[PDB]
Image (cartoon, rainbow, N blue to C red):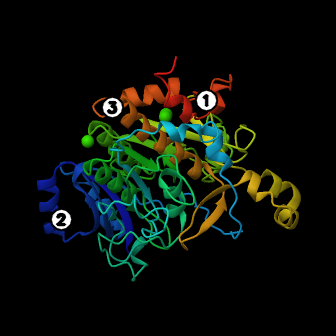
Amino acid sequence: EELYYSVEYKNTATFNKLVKKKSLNVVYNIPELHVAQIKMTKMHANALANYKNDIKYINATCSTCITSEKTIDRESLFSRQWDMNKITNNGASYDDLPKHANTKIAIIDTGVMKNHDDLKNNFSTDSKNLVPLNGFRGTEPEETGDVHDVNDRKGHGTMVSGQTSANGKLIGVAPNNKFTMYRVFGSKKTELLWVSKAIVQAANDGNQVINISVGSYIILDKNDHQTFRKDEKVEYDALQKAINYAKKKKSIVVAAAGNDGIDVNDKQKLKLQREYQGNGEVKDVPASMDNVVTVGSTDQKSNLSEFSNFGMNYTDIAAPGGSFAYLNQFGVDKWMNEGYMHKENILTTANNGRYIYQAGTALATPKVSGALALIIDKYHLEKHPDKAIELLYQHGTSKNNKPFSRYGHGELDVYKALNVANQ
Ligand SMILES: [Ca+2]
Ligand SMILES: [Ca+2]
Ligand SMILES: [Ca+2]
């Protein structure tokens, strides 16, 4: 039987010549990162590893590494956006939006309902599909591989897009900015290599803010210097390199903290997310990677959400993503018949053309991406993205002495970020 292997090669020309020689079935490729995915028997994988001149590393593509998203519709009544009110001084910052909304926000996710009334004006036709023909491990025969197909099957990407860009009945953080969707999910799982390719594409398409509202726990064993490996180094290195490539193109990567309420500095707890007893470590990625704005989630009381991961040398900032504390406490019947979803959940755009109440770090993250786009445009920082990040942290966070280990630089404050001239 054949398995899917992640491969990091050394040279395009020599790798291509090797592919011809052995008739390797390459199922995905990312030339900018010298990484490809090959379907082959375990024996041919071992053999392929002996070509030290053309092959750097090889590892089986991780099956159970990506964390599952949440789109379950547990709605009809349309309430107010308490979460936006918390970061805009109760709507006062909408009067301070830049006149020229030039920055484009890329969103790497499940797709988007491009004709949603609140999202259509801001949807960019640069949007692209990174899901390959036949989808995940070739088990989705309905995935044509059509580069223009970014329709949202799962519903998550539409939720995220509303937070950055709704401009109608719902209002996102950057309602005048264009957003670009890079679809990396069909109807099943995604592959971190697709996410990596999406990052490269988003950067090449000139999106100065790149939002990744999904994450995974990956196994990395730095002590192992072998070519054929048991960890997931190819995926780890590819993702980190894509992020650094984005940085090189002057794009900012914003990622969601994991949604397991874990202190990422507690090794025992991280390893438990992959039931890993090996030598290496489990890492929350891309949240913990270099050059990533790591976003945690807060609730309606400005406290860290019970599901938000956090930690020293991890969390950079926090924004409202909601909570299920009332639900988990009282049960669905009392929670629902008594309208608690209107108090602790985030109201957002849904792929049915209407709206949905949800919660998660995936809904906090786009608020920060939107804020960065506003900062870049307000202060004309296109040529100096690091200055936009610095401004976000210094002037785009409320000062309430929240511990840095849980909230990073603080809770997002868009009104403050847009009023630096005011002093
Ligand atoms: Ca660029
Ligand atoms: Ca780190
Ligand atoms: Ca970070």
Examine the rendered structure and indicate whether residue 264 appears above or below residue 162.
above
**Residue 357 on image: x %, y %:** 67, 61
Q: Is mark 3 within 8 Å of ligand 1?
A: no
Task: Say which quarter of the image contains residue 342.
Answer: bottom right
Q: What amino acid is at disc 1?
A: Gly
**Which mark is in front, 3 or 2?**
3
Q: Is residue 288 visible?
A: no
* Residue 19: mark: 2
SS class, disc 1 = loop
Q: What amino acid is at disc 3?
A: His
SS class, disc 3 = loop
SS class, disc 2 = helix
- Residue sticking out furthest to the front: 95
Name the residue tied to disc 3. Answer: 380
**Residue 55 on image: x %, y %:** 24, 51
- Residue sticking out furthest to the bottom: 141
Circle 3 residues within 10 Å: few <14, some 14–19, many ≥20? some
Residue 214 lies left or right of residue 320; in this view the side is left
Examine the rendered structure and indicate whether residue 76 appears above or below residue 51.
below
Circle 1 residues within 10 Å: few <14, some 14–19, many ≥20? many
**Residue 77 on image: x %, y %:** 71, 67
Instruction: Give the Cα separation between the discs numbered 3 and 2.
Output: 46 Å
Q: Is residue 409 visible?
A: yes
Could you tell me which residue is drawn at 42 percent across and 56 percent down?
Answer: 108
* Residue 177 or residue 225, whichever sits in front: 177
Could you tell me which residue is drawn at 32 percent across and 52 percent down?
Answer: 202
* Residue 44 or residue 129, whichever sits in front: 129
Circle 2 residues within 10 Å: few <14, some 14–19, many ≥20? some
* Residue 410: mark: 1
First in sequence: mark 3 vs mark 2: 2
**Which mark is in front, 2 or 1?**
1
Marker count (numbered): 3
